[PDB]
Image (spheres, coloured by chain):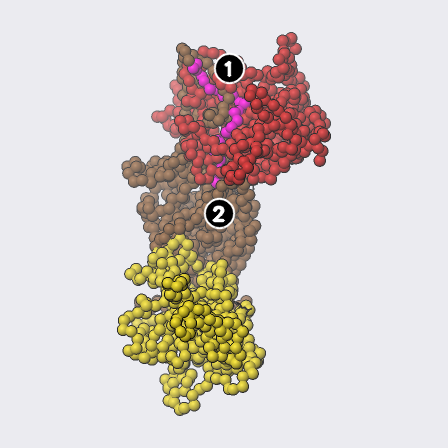
Chain colours: A yellow, B brown, C red
Amino acid sequence: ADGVGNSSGNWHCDSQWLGDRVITTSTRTWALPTYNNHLYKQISSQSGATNDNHYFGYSTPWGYFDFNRFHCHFSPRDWQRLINNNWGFRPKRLNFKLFNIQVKEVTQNDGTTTIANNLTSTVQVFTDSEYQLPYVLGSAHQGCLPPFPADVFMVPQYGYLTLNNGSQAVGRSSFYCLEYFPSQMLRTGNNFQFSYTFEDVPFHSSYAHSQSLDRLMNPLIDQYLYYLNRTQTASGTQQSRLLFSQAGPTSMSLQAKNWLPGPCYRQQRLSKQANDNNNSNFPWTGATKYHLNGRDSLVNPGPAMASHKDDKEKFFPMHGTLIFGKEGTNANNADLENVMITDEEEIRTTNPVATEQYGTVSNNLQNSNAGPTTGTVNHQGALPGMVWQDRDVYLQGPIWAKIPHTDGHFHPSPLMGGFGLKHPPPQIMIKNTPVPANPPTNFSAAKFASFITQYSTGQVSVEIEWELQKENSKRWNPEIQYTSNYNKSVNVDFTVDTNGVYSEPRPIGTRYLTRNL
Amino acid sequence: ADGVGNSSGNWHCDSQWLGDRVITTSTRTWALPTYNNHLYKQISSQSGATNDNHYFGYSTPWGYFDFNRFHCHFSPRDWQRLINNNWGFRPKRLNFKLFNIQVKEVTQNDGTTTIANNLTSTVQVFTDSEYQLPYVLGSAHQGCLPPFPADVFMVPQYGYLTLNNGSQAVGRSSFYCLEYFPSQMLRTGNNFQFSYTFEDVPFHSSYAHSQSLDRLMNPLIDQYLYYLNRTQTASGTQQSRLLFSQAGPTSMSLQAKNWLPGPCYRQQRLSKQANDNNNSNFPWTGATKYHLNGRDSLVNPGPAMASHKDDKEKFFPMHGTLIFGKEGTNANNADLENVMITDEEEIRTTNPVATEQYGTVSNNLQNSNAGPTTGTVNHQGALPGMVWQDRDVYLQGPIWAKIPHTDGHFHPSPLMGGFGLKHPPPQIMIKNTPVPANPPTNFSAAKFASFITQYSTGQVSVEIEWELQKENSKRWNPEIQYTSNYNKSVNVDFTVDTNGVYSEPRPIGTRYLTRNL
Amino acid sequence: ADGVGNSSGNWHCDSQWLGDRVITTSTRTWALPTYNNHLYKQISSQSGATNDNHYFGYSTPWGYFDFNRFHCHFSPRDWQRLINNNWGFRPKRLNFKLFNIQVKEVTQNDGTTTIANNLTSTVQVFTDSEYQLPYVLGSAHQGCLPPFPADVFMVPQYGYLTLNNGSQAVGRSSFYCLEYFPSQMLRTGNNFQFSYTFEDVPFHSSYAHSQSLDRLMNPLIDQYLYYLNRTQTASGTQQSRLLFSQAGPTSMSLQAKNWLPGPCYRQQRLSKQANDNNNSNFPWTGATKYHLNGRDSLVNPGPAMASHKDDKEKFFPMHGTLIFGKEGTNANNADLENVMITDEEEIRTTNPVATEQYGTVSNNLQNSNAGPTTGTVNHQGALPGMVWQDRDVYLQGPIWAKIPHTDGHFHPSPLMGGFGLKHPPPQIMIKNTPVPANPPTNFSAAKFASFITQYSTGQVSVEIEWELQKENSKRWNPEIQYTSNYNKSVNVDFTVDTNGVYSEPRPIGTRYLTRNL
Ligand SMILES: Nc1ncnc2c1ncn2[C@H]1C[C@H](O)[C@@H](COP(=O)(O)O)O1
Ligand SMILES: Nc1ncnc2c1ncn2[C@H]1C[C@H](O)[C@@H](COP(=O)(O)O)O1
Ligand SMILES: Nc1ncnc2c1ncn2[C@H]1C[C@H](O)[C@@H](COP(=O)(O)O)O1
């Protein structure tokens, strides 16, 4: 209830730190085109694609808003405060607003374009509260709010996939008409709002451990539990004998322990230094992949596993980490120097190394005649007594994902990162209401193909309230912090360049502060 | 009381199932042109048309809204729920809204068109509550709301017919000026609404019978009523004698029965297989037709009668069923493969077969000299003790019709299908108020032929509340349900194609669940 | 709550006349066997039967009680009181009881049978209130309570028919397990009861008319309406001329009249005198029949139509009347003297004669050249202004029938006779609970084929309250009454013979008293 000449909202970008919680707000400007001429179209993989790449689905005229990346809600400085001072954080509740809507009509005459306000035109917005539509958010697609507030972004088109057989469609394939959901219709002067409250979810670990999993022992004291030291006599004629000893400071690897490392599903190892890697093409052939319904699919990034062992910085697991492009990077065949490869190194203390075997097991029964042989375990599922760390969340990266609705889920934490949610923040859908062009003067029952070309722009605000977990540590010596380099440079990190382009030089994980196991 | 910049309504398309009742809402976008230059014109059949095809009437600038098809209010899934779980349904009350009106003015300069908002222009809407205008709704014309919500449709022009003699007009011919009815005038920011309540009407049968009409007997037990078994001696010299017997399980056709099949008016039989039908042109000549005021008219589809007898799927009665076109079908001379021919087969148990005689009667009085002869009854009116089923309603098909106001009506159920109503949902009329172009500067009493070319678009919502009748059956074995084929296919049924075109592959009747007679 | 040694009910057979209403009670003794070894079996027509006689269905172990014949509730004297003194009667409410149950176990050793009380054995009884089972009552099957109270009858087996194609079964065929309905289980000392209330139903006509339909005129006075007396000049050279006259006492057939006779569907005429009928076999071939779903079925007895015209007592319509056998009559090929053929003669005044045409209509358009020709109408459906009488109810004959549940019914009065009911008196089902014989001593999952042979007997009471409509007539002269012949005879009518066999010598209609139209 405003009208043409009254702004329907204000610009709120600030972040405020209450010290129990942080409330981060982001207001951005957006532009929504008219997708595929107001038409639902089915889409399917082109025949000739490999079996693994077939798909069947539907593309819709609707757009949608996704804030699911962290840097939407945090400036690099606000991110620094969080990761430096806190052991954990989780989202509590969010608030969403659309305001200052403008709908522009576009005419094209000869080689000139003309844009004019359409004051009576309408835009449609609905949030899906009941999760009745396919949920495309957690797939780490582009189209999220820009990192830098002054940027204007384009609203991505909404489309979804369903069951397929080859490129065809089985009878269970669902078709969803989004025009079948009650949606609010807005003009210039109308605004949209809703609130949301996150369900209870474990704090993310903002900490790295100060202890290895196998080192929890007291280094001074000797155990009371014996282990088998010798299966053979030490001196004289070699003879079979069983000899036992108490494990202690000198040999730690031999002691009894209460816990096991997290589950492993092994990765191939790549070398950053050129010419060290094998010469052959094996992203697909030599990879680790899961076979689902006759289709192979990479395991990416996969179960959380340390990227590299001690003193091996150069190597990284193939398809085992999140990779981010630097500004201006091609979407096809970018060089290693252009991408930013994240590192899981903090989880060494519990999780296995992604490129190394889980361990070793005995594959036979020995006797006097047959010597003991042992097999190598390259994949291990959960065993009683395992402990593990989840993959780290970055400044740019998924905040949440929707736990698929199924009978069973095991440790439902998104494998890209973030907060697994059964009821994730709803999908906000938006489209431009069709405006017909001049109808014929004699009735025809054919459907209109003739529409006025138009688009809409506006403002969007997202306010999320994040709960914090403070550092209680008694650690004497100084902890690692995330710091900016003091040395001079042509450009400042996390800042626009001479041409106005915002860029993020490096990925920033959240794990700096240290805790004990 | 809104203004230019406030939307006058919201988009509500949903359906909600309360389990006693279902409330189905449909919101669509429409475009209304300017019909025949704001002029009432009389229309009449061109001389040279056959006597049967003459007409006389009037075409009006007004448009109108018709939701009278089912699929307007039901998605194919909502239709599946209804027909599978319910023995009957009837409409209770509806609610209608027009909102977000836009009036566009169109100029044409050289080969370029230009469309701009006319903010002060008006649209006129009135509902006819008192049924004072001719009622054109129940005639199964095009122009109803589209099946699929995302489509935009064109509002059909309103015109009506009255008495004629040849192509001329008798003095009783009525002329109705719709500009003579109080109507509401709306600008952008004004909206229109009314409510309606259906009169008590019999539930439609959503069921098929589990028994034939002639099989209601107990198959185990023998009757106490005798019938005439033999008019002649069984053995020896043939002699006239009357012999009686009790009819029983062995011969059921001979038993006494309390009820008769529904009335029959016979149809010609056609074969779907090419070359089986006769070679000659007889849609008109060999048809079944009623002769009214010197004009022949087909009986279409006609009294409800079963389409075919047992084990004769290929044949169908000529002009005896509803026929729907598949998407993209020509309106002229479409092949049998393009049309969708509905089937009345469920009513075999009571109604006669449309292509078969009603029965046989005796045309003489026998004696010893004259043997009994008997005539064939090809048409039968109501006899005491008849029972019959009404024609089935489809997903696309008439919901209601207006029972003509007359002294007498017999079983006033529309012969196309649906709910006969004495006070059907009113007609909603709409037109664009004329806007003159620049008048001359010297007074002339001639009428304006000079108008600003313009059209209007907007939004329309229809909310109907349907009452349901639940299945009480004790049937042990599983009932037939309407199911989608599981096998894979290029396209999914009841879904858009690659080019964005919504299509309905087959007509869906409501009769699946079974009841006893 | 009685036990072995307490009778659970008393014998009430009396009838009592309150003069507004009559309350007739009937108590009888019954015996229920074990039908088809406790098994549901499907039953179907044997292949080789004619198309018309095919059926498909199920036979159940359950029995049932049917009182639907009149003489169950009325003695011949109570029937005489009713039909003589009353213009109409209809049922109001009934009350039903089962009591004094006895279950007997039967062993057979060599050629000797032994019957002993099983005190712990159970019988199952349920009434179907919701009409969920097939309703087999109105089909005029045997098994009703005997006419004469001292007789003991056997409870008939319950089985039902459903859709068939040939002798096979279409997927819509319903199977009903009666063991799926909550039923009361009784031992000796338990009794069963329920009450029922008939829905409002028209009084049956107990009267015959004192006037013909075409004679309602004043015989003294001449009409003011002219009719066409002469189409040709009376004298001189014959010339076309139209001459009109007022119809009056001399010619009554020519007068204008307000009403038409009831609808006719014509019957073949048979002669009771031997050798007068044609010599050939035509019960099936020369009959009147309705064709339903590719099967012919006789119309029996058919729409109510007078049996014979004035002074033609000997002839009767073929399949047009109810026929009852005299005591001791064969069920196959009984002679004309053994059967009792009912007569509809009372309805002459309105209904057409079953063996005569309805009338005559003109089949062409005359001119000077073409003389008028006219067709004969052998079948007529309802026309505005028709009046008709329903078929008469006899002392032995159907009381009611269930109006099939369908969309439309026309004058739903059973064509055998009686009271059409949408909610007829419920079906009372009964069976003997299975008692296994000694099981094997080692578990086997096969079903028991081994049962203790047993049957049950007991008492059944039916009390119906009938409402009466008194004679108001001013008729001066004495009306016909139903009287017993005074002349002496070897046996008395409606009485046992020397051998103890009750017999009914003649059918007794209810129409004696006369009313005006
Ligand atoms: N990311 C995520 N989302 C939801 N549930 C999770 C997740 N990770 C683990 N779990 C499950 C399994 C943990 O033992 C438990 C901790 O819940 P607590 O709240 O700590 O009592 O919740
Ligand atoms: N379609 C339709 N509309 C209106 N009236 C109809 C229709 N079909 C039948 N009838 C009439 C004739 C029925 O016997 C009666 C049932 O009304 P009931 O409500 O079941 O008591 O109503
Ligand atoms: N046998 C039978 N059962 C049910 N309905 C019937 C029957 N015969 C006729 N009718 C219908 C048609 C009559 O015009 C009306 C009289 O109902 P009234 O009660 O007299 O107002 O009821």
Disc number placed over residue C336 in the picture, else none: 1
Could you tell me which chain the residue with mark 2 belongs to? B
* Image-based side of C150 in relation to A177, left or right: right
> Which residue appears at 53% of the width and 40% of the height?
C443
Give the camera-side residue of B240 and B221. Answer: B221
Disc number placed over residue B245 in the picture, else none: none
Q: Is residue C166 visible?
A: yes
Q: Which residues are magenta?
A: B208-234
> Which residue appears at 40% of the width and 21% of the height?
B373
Quarter holding the N terminus of chain B is bottom right
Residue A119 drawn above or below residue A54: below
Question: Quadrant of the rendered structure where residue C72 is?
Answer: top right
> Which residue appears at 63% of the width and 11% of the height?
C498
x%, y% of residue C465?
A: 67, 30
Question: Quadrant of the rendered structure where residue C150 is?
Answer: top right
Circle 2 sits on which residue?
A: B84
- In this view, the residue farthest toward the bottom is A488
Element under disc 2: helix
Kind of residue indicated by mark 1: Leu
Mark 1: few/some/many CA within 10 Å (<14, 14-19, 20+):
some
Residue A131 drawn above or below residue A278: above
x%, y% of residue C120?
A: 65, 33
Could you tell me which chain the residue with mark 1 belongs to? C
- In this view, the residue farthest toward the left is A279
Q: Is residue C260 visible?
A: no
Kind of residue indicated by mark 2: Asn
x%, y% of residue C154?
A: 59, 25
Give the dominant element type of the magenta stretch: helix, strand or loop.
loop
Residue A504 drawn above or below residue C336: below
